[PDB]
Amino acid sequence: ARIFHFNSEVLTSPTMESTLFKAIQWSKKFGGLIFFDLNLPLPLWRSRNETRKLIKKSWDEANIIEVSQQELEFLLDEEYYERRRNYTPQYFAEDFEQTKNRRDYYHYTPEEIKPLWHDDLKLLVVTDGTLRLHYYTPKFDGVVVGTEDVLITPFTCDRTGSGDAVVAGIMRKLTTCPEMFEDQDVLERQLRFAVAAGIISQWTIGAVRGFPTESATQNLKEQVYVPSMW
Amino acid sequence: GEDATVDKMCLERFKVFLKQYNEWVEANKDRLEEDSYKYDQDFYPGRRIRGK
Image (cartoon, rainbow over all chains, first blue to last red; front, top):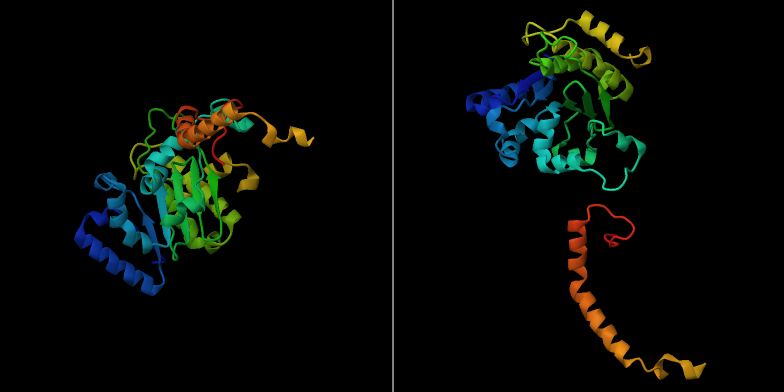
């Protein structure tokens, strides 16, 4: 295996925690990459500091990390970003775009990400569903603009498994495109594939039943984006 | 000229006002800025000049 993938659900079991760390040792010995897909279960949303202490070791043992916007903001500070979203200028906007009252797609600075960064981390991806994919590398950072339409099929849409499809697409492009870790344009172009994979996965009832194929995902990616973004 | 220098002025009542004003300013300066931050979210001309 070239990528080792696990979730934070194993951290809720001590046996699985010890087995996970032994398996991570074995995988790092043979040259594999460690993919931490947080997916915080219900117990791990109790408090920030407890979850940080629980996940710090596995967090530091990971080369690739995927968290949702809610998970990242819970791990850093929930109330600060909640207040920041609710802020409205009192007299006039600071630019024309602030007048449109659009949905907030705030891109966290690497200075804000600094507490969660470590030396072996090659790629951090923050996902606002399929709408935004904030990526952070030791060299650069940015956001991939995506979309969603579950209203196109109101009676078959189901969001279960969409994040699994996004993570699977990320791994699929990482295993075959090593330049993603070092080239920003290539990274965004390959992350649009995972965006498309997540979009398709929301159109079917059932996670496993609705997982897209590579052909359908590439077709949707080429249909949604303009040809220069492929 | 030298007959209009400040030392020759008779402004003792104004000096008493000045010392009382300075005492009040030094005692109340920070509370006013805290109240301005608490009551006025954004700065506008006519508001209290605060911060840097």
